[PDB]
Structure formats: structure tokens, C-alpha cells
Amino acid sequence: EIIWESLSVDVGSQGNPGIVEYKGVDTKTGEVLFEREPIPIGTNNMGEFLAIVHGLRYLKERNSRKPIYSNSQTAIKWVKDKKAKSTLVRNEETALIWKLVDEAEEWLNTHTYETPILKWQTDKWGEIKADY
RNA sequence: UCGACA
DNA sequence: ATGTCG
Ligand SMILES: [Mg+2]
Ligand SMILES: [Mg+2]
Image 1: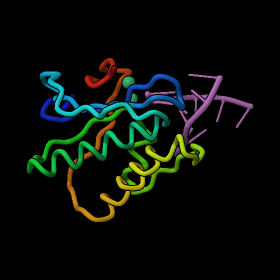
Image 2 (image 1 turned 120 degrees about the horizontal axis):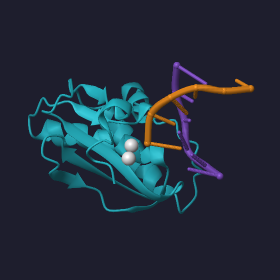
Image 3 (image 1 turned 90 degrees about the vertical axis):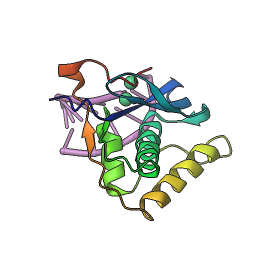
């Protein structure tokens, strides 16, 4: 009951808050389909969220109906809500991540999608394929 | 008072 | 250690 015909996304960091990156992979093959350049300060949950939204945009642009897997219950909720409820402080070091979060929410509020966003069941299936 | 996902 | 929700 793993839907192999899917995109898996995940965050990586150094610190939390700290340097954040994320990527998207083909769940079947492991092939890296997109990878974001490291953002100097952000949170895990912000990155998990940006990964999902990147994935929605990636699949939409390519007319793909594949679902997206994420391991992040937080991010899955933020995407469903179109709203990332982060605590991270706003200052000049966090301005970049907060601009990207704001632009992701804005994309969600201006586009449609029917991509199923699914929880990757780590406890049964091991680490998601996009794990760092 | 936790439980869970990262 | 921290970020987040049920
Ligand atoms: Mg994750
Ligand atoms: Mg991971």
C-alpha cells in the first residue's frame, strides 16, 4: 500500500533553527527531481512545508497527477490550511525563509490542484525516500 | 499532564 | 537540544 507512482519530499537541516534545504525524489527510483539551495536560517517545519508546495508546483507545471508523500504531520496541515503557523522570529537573518513561506502561501491561494498529499508511514516503511 | 510527527 | 500538532 505504498503508492510507488508518487513524488516524495523532505527537509534537511544543520541546526533547527538553522540552515535549511529540501528536495523531491521519485518514490520508485530515488531519482532527485528538484533540490533547493540551502536557506541560511529556517525551521524544520518551514522547510517541510516549502518542500510540499514546491512539489505541488513541480507536478502542476508537468501536468502530473502523482500524489506527494511527506513525513511531516505539521507541514501537511499547513498546506491543507494554506497557512504556515511558524514561531520563528522575523529579523533580517530570517527574512529570506519568511519571504519564501509567504510566496508559497500565496501560490496556494492562487492555484488549484488535486494532488493527494499523503503521510509517509515511517514506522512501517522506513525513512522516506527523500530523507537526507 | 502528556501523546505524536519531524 | 528545537519545531510543531492532537
Ligand atoms: Mg521529514
Ligand atoms: Mg527526514
